[PDB]
Amino acid sequence: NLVQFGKMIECAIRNRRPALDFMNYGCYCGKGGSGTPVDDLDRCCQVHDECYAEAEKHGCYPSLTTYTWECRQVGPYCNSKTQCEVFVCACDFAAAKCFAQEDYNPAHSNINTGERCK
């Protein structure tokens, strides 16, 4: 669920920035979901959106999913059981690792998505 994804980001990126930074960034970081991603970080978010949308297509509801995971020395680690929770944990896991790897450009935060993401 939302809080878990937040804690998972924090874990992956070693609390280098607030998880809240990833909620208003580029064309895809935040809720939905259009145009060309402004950079590879934003593309993390696009792939994440696609992942959730696959999950929902198959009967999961990512916003209602509370999965099982742990923050380990090596990073976030999914330890879920049911199909949906395994699927949704793995969406969040790939996005969090992606965020840890990619550059965060402050000029790409809080962009006019109305105008720049069509």
Image: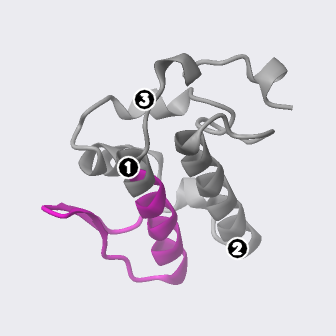
Q: Label 2, on which residue?
A: 59
Is 79 covered by the magenta stretch?
A: yes
Neighbour tally class for label 1: few under 14, some 14-19, many 20 plus, Cα within 10 Å: some
What's the magenta region?
Answer: 67-96
Which residue is at a point 60% across and 35% down the rendered structure image? 30
Question: From the viewer's perspective, is 70 left or right of 116?
Answer: left
Q: Circle 2 — which element? A: loop
Earlier in the chain: of badge 2 and badge 1, it is 2
Q: Circle 1 — which element? A: helix
- The label nearer to you, 2 versus 3, is 3
- The label nearer to you, 2 versus 1, is 1
Task: Verify CB contact (< 8 Å) between mark 1 and mark 3.
Answer: no
Question: From the viewer's perspective, is 109 left or right of 101?
Answer: right
| Residue 39 % position (x, y) | 60, 38
| Colour approach in the figure | one colour
| Residue 57 % position (x, y) | 76, 70
Measure the alpha-carbon separation of dots 1 and 3: 17 Å
Q: Circle 3 — which element? A: helix
Which residue is at a point 78% across and 23% down the rendered structure image? 116
Earlier in the chain: of badge 1 and badge 3, it is 3
| Residue 63 % position (x, y) | 57, 53
Measure the alpha-carbon separation of dots 2 and 1: 30 Å
Compared to residue 29, the image places residue 7 above or below, namely: below
Q: Which mark is residue 20?
A: 3
Depth order, front residue of 81/17: 17
Task: Verify CB contact (< 8 Å) between mark 2 and mark 3.
Answer: no
Depth order, front residue of 44/92: 44
Q: Label 1, on which residue?
A: 101
